[PDB]
Image (spheres, coloured by chain):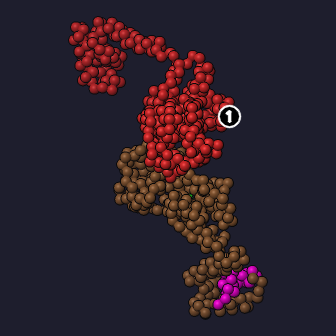
Chain colours: A red, B brown
Amino acid sequence: MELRHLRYFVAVVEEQSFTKAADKLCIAQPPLSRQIQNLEEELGIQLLERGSRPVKTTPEGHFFYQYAIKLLSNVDQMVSMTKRIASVEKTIRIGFVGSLLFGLLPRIIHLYRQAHPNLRIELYEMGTKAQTEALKEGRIDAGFGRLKISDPAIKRTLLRNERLMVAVHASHPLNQMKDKGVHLNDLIDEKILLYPSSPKPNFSTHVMNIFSDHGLEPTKINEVREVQLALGLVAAGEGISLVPASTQSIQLFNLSYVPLLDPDAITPIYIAVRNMEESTYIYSLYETIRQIYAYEGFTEPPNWL
Amino acid sequence: MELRHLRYFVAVVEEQSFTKAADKLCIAQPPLSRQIQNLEEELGIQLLERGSRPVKTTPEGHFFYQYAIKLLSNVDQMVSMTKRIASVEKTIRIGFVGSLLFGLLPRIIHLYRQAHPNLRIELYEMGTKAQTEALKEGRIDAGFGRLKISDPAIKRTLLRNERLMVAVHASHPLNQMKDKGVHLNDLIDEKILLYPSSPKPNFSTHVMNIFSDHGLEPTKINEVREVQLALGLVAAGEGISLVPASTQSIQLFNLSYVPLLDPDAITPIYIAVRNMEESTYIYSLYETIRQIYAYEGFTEPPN
Ligand SMILES: [Cl-]
Ligand SMILES: [Cl-]
């Protein structure tokens, strides 16, 4: 038998009518009656005095109603009880892009971590496209990326614009311009290393937008898998690359970082959250970004609160 | 006739009586009435209602008044302009891109002409790359553009960030969001008409960039010759199109413009001058823009 068999019987007994029971179940009278019939023909006992109005129970049905109500109610309790032991431990899932690993994100996470010793924190290297998908889908709670998001269900805050830099070998003509800087236009015809080869749109997309925003489109490009390969290939003299300033966490012999003069040769750092987000766990993260930044001397991101 | 007659005629219609107009000019009304009489016979047409004392003008008389306030207003401009001329004749050459003709540019230029009555201004339509190599060579002295410029021989300053908008046929579903606007995301699958088809970079580049900033690369795209075509075709039920806000200068039956909600769905406007530029004419140009920008409630920059 079914619980549906029971809920139907119970609705008929209480209402003492087949109509007030089918309407309160939002079903038709025929299927309702047929199911209780199927219940009776399965038990071998008649529960209802059918034909006598208002509908009432057989003595056997009168006992069955009492056990049925309890059993339905114990199903209700089971479900509830089962839901009480489940899902105690709070988890915050944070998505981020690999390039952000060389900046402040780690120390930010560590601090937030000290602030919440009872919180499970899961970290996932993901791109902005996946982050947006994972956010809307609940899979993550806060994303960090370099590429703006086109999606109304999501909200981006710009945390800080970060300066682009030209990684060059030490013998390169441009290295003579290390102190002062070069312009994007000075790079236009060099072999340029773009990275990562990871799913678009990634940092290579951004670099190209920067050149395109400045009327430029370099033909000598060569996409490479990762940032260390970029730098590594540069320090072997394959060519130049464009990297965030924070990437200067990586120093390789004869690898020389060189500023850009173009006021808009910048890569922004965003935090993305679901549009209607309000967890104190995210604001606490946000506050932690504000705390670290001031500590470091960057301008603070604006008020959540 | 003489200016006397027009001035004399102006006061009688401004101040509605013969004696009250005579008070304004501090002269006798016996000859004043003769002068206005002397005007109508020369024309061979009456200008005022014969005997009516409210007072009021005739069909042809009223038209003449407005013509007169315009002429008299220009004789003052003749007087005022002639005192502040310049030195026999300089030429300032200005480069701009076509899309700027729909915004505040021509009104800036028009008011600029007024500051320098004797100045020969020379307008040249050209894209950014061409404005660069033209400023470096002296062939222009300012360049109004929509593209960023890796300098360094060139100083550019951001004047304003014009909103982008989506041109759509009024039947299009997006047109529901006419007073609420949309996001680029909604355009991902749309038929998008990019303009123009000149040498790149140009506005199409920019739009392809704007989409790129946001992690979007549309596939259903056509590049068309220019803005009118793009709009024309949008009306012709051919697709959608991304325009600067000022394109709404062009209005077509069943065309409607949807605003974009994305914060960076924008088209910047830059003046570009030679790095070491301190000419008074250019400084003057800067201030006209600030003058105009102020008038329209927009932001002034430290130029
Ligand atoms: Cl960082
Ligand atoms: Cl404008």
Residue B22 on the magenta span:
yes
What is the quadrant of residue A66 in the picture? top left
Q: Position of residue A106 (x, y in %)?
A: 57, 26
Q: In which quarter of the image is the N terminus of chain A?
A: top left
- Identify the residue under disc 1: A297
Q: Where is residue A36 in the image (x, y as percent from the top left)?
A: 26, 16
At x 48%, y 26%, the residue is A124
Find the magenta span and give its range.
B1-24
Query: The residue under label 1 is which amino acid type?
Result: Gly
Q: Which residue lies furthest to the front in this view?
A: A171
Assign a secondary structure to mark 1: loop
Tell me if I can see residue A127 in this picture.
no
* Residue B212 percent coordinates (x, y): 46, 44
Front-lying residue, A43 or B10:
B10
Does the magenta run of residues contain B190?
no
| Left or right of B54 on screen, residue A138 | left
Q: Residue at point 64% right, 73% down? A: B90
How many labels, in total?
A: 1
Q: Is residue A120 above or below residue B38?
A: above
For image coordinates 35% across by 24% down, the residue present is: A24
Depth check: A155 or A305 in front?
Answer: A155
The structure residue drawn at horizontal position 54% and vertical position 34%, both measured from the top left corner, is: A271
Q: Residues within 10 Å of mark 1 (few under 14, many from 20)?
A: few
Q: Which secondary structure type mostly characterizes the magenta part of the structure?
A: helix
Q: Residue A44 location in percent, x, y?
A: 22, 8
Image quadrant in which you'd find residue B162? bottom right
Q: The numbered mark 1 sits on a residue in which chain?
A: A
